[PDB]
Image: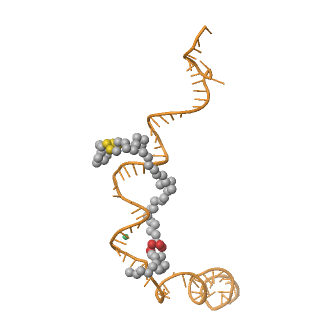
Amino acid sequence: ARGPAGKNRGVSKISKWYKADDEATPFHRRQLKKATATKLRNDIAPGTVLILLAGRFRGKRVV
RNA sequence: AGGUCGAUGAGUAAGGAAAUGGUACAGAACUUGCUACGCCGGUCAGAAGACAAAAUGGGUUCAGAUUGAAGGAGUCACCUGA
Ligand SMILES: [Mg+2]
C-alpha cells in the first residue's frame, strides 16, 4: 500500500468520467413526499383501556 | 485535296481541393508523474425481488353527518282573541 494522498489521487477513476445511464431512474417529485403527520382517535385517552385485537396477546384489555 | 466538332494530353492558371508542401488543432509512441485496474472486506450513499400491514395524498365513485341564503297566493299555517 501507499499512504501519500496527492491532489493527484482520485480524479482519474472510471467513476467520474463514466456513468451507466441505461437504467430507468424514478424521478423526484416535491408534491408527493412532502406531507406527514400522526393522529389519535378521540376515544384514545392517556391511560385508557385498549382492546388488543391482532396481537400474540390479542383478546386482552390493556393500558 | 480542303474546313469544322470530337477523343487522347504537354502546358496554363480561373474554379476546386483528392495527391505534395505549410500552418493550426490534438488522440497516439515517447518522457515526467505515488495513481489507474481488478478480487475480496466492511461503511456511507443511490437503487432495491415476492407477498403483505400501516400512514399520507390524487383521479373515478359510494356512503353517513352539518350550516347559510333566496323564493314561494311575499307560500300555507299556529298561538293571544271581540
Ligand atoms: Mg463492494
- What residue is at 47 percent from the left and 72 percent from the top? A16
The quadrant of the picture showing ligand 1 is bottom left
Say which residue appears at 41% left-offset and 80% top-offset: A3
User: Residue placed at 35% from the left, 42% from the top?
Assistant: A49
Give the total number of marks visible in the rendering. Answer: 0
Q: Could one spot residue A22 in this view of the protein?
A: yes
Can you give x and y, in whole percent of width and height, for residue B4 in the image? 69, 83
> On the rendered structure, is A38 left or right of B77?
left
**Of the pair B76 and B37, the residue shown nearer to us:** B76
Residue B46's place in the image compared with B56, above or below, is below
Res B41 → quadrant: bottom left
Tell which residue pokes out farthest to the front in this image.
A47
Quadrant where the N terminus of chain A sits is bottom left
Establish if B38 lies above or below B33. Answer: above
Q: Position of residue B39 (x, y in %)?
A: 34, 74
> Please, is residue A21 above or below residue A36 in the view?
below
Image quadrant where one finds the C terminus of chain A: top left
Relative image position of residue A8 (x, y in whole percent)? 48, 80
- The x, y position of residue B55, in whole percent, is 42, 48
A62 vs B11, nearest the viewer: A62
Q: Is residue A53 visible?
A: no
Q: Residue at x 37, y 42 (%)?
A: A48
Which coloring applies here?
Answer: secondary structure
Relative to B9, A51 lies left or right? left
Which sits in the foreground, B53 or B5?
Answer: B53
